[PDB]
Structure formats: structure tokens, C-alpha cells
Length: 96
Length: 187
Image (cartoon, one colour):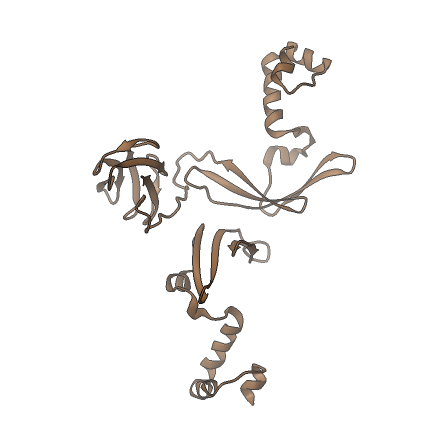
């Protein structure tokens, strides 16, 4: 009940023991997954380090599905302390 | 007859005595006018200083006609020392390339070599370029020295892996190099 109330929907028997065995950790894994998604798919050097300027990285999402990302530049922090990363993803200009 | 030949076509009487009076200066005014447009329309602070990161500026072109320009970011220089300015003009994304007058080209970022491409020669480890021995469009033998780099008070020359022609040299004398930097391309 508790997991199906926190997450609101699908919960497996794997989720249940995972929570019982590691309450704090399971929960924290969900918060991270909610934010960044499936991090297993990223390659290790991209996972630990991110990306350099003018780099292109492939991420195999499925059979014949993959993300193509190019990191162009990163801006200087603004007044709020926020930097603008200029991206190119799947032939589409993107800003984060 | 002279001025109309040089320029596009339209020349006024005011153009003519402006030349006569100040030949070289008038001819310079035209070269700048052809390069940058009408600078007198710029506000003075912008005219002398350009723009700071994140600044929005207005240029009164005429009644109801103005340029709203925002300077978003200035990139690090490429191997040629060309910085990419990220602009916003009248709600349109815009990119402009400007050559940086460095002094020493140690701020230049070289693209990484493609390790699967045999044409691409990459830097084995970090150093500085001591001597460039080839230029673009030069046929070279196998084992021919084509770049001398210094690591840690140690010189190690880079040589051609096969017979071929140089497509690009991304480095000049005194430039810093990093592990994996593209340096040469050959056929």
C-alpha cells in the first residue's frame, strides 16, 4: 500500500523486499530515478564525468533506438547562479 | 566614374568631394561601411565596448525599425582561435564567428581525434608543440617526422604512419596539446 501510495501505480514484489531490506536507500533511488531516469544505459565515462565541449555521445535506449547528444558549450553562471548548456539532441537544438 | 566602378553604383555629389578632400580616409570609410554597416546608429557605450554576457541592447535603425540584440555566451576559441558568439536578434537564434587576437595561442581548444579513423593522428600525451614540420597539402613518406612536441623537458617527434597527403594541421609552434587531441590528418 505504502509504495503504491508514494509512487502512485505499479509496484513489483522486487520493490517490496528492496524497500524492506534498505528503506532509506530504496526511497533515495526512486527520487533519483524520478529525476534522471534509467542511468544504467549511460556509458561509464559519461556517467562519472559527463561530457566535454564538442563531444558526441550515443546511448542505446532499445534495439535500434538510441540518443545522440552533442554538448556545444556551457555558459557563465547568471545572477541566480545558473549556467546554460547548449545541446544538440536527435537533430534538435536544446537548452538546459 | 571612379567611385561608381569601385562601389555598387549609387554615388552622390557629397560622396565625390568627400573623396577628393580625403581620398584615403573616404576609401577607408567605405571599407568599414561595407564590413560593418552604419556604425553611427549604435549608442556610444556599445560602439566603444560591445556587449557583456547577458546584455540586451537596442539599435534605432529608423522610425519603428530597431534591432534588439542579446549576447548569450562567448565560446572558447577553436584551434584557429575563432570564438563563437551566441546571439539573439529580434527573437532569432544567431551564431557569429570572431577571430581572437590572443598573443599566445594556448587558449585554443583542439577537437578530439577519432580513434577508429586511421587518417586521424592524436596526441599520445600532454605537451607543447615545439616544431611543425609539414603544412596542409604536402605529400609525405612513411616514418617521416611531421611534428615535434615536448612532454616534460623531453622531445618526441610524431611521424607519418603511411604514404599520404596532409588534410589538416591543427597546431602551430608553442601551442598546448592534451591527450587525444587531433594534430594531423593524412590520406
